Amino acid sequence: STECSNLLLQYGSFCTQLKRALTGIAVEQDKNTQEVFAQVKQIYKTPPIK
Amino acid sequence: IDRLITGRLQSLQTYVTQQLIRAAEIRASANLAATKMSECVLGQSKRVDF
Image 1 (cartoon, one colour):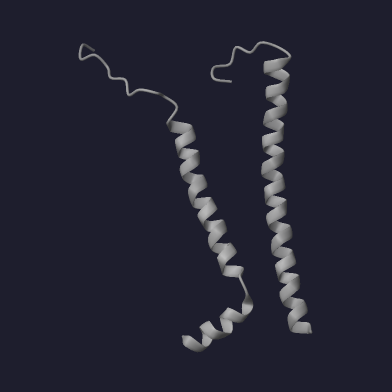
Image 2 (cartoon, rainbow over the protein chains, first blue to last red):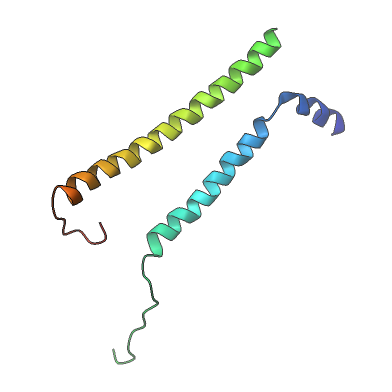
C-alpha cells in the first residue's frame, strides 16, 4: 500500500534498527556454530582397519 | 504533543532495552575475563585450550 508506506515513513528508523538486530542475531548463530564445532585444524581420517 | 511524546518515549524505551541486553552480554564476558585472570595468571591450569 502506497498510502500506508507514506504514513510509515513518518515513524522514523525503527525498522532499520529492527533489521540490524535481526542481522546481528543471524550472524551470531553462525558464530556460535563455528565456535562450537570448528575447533580442529585438520580433517583427520580413520585408518581402514577397524 | 501527545503523539510526539508517545514516539519519543517508545524510542527511549527501545534504547534502554538494547542497553540492558548489551550490559548482560558485557557482564558475561567480564566474568569470563575475571576467571581467566584468576586461573591463568595467578596459577597454572590443566584445562585444555583454556
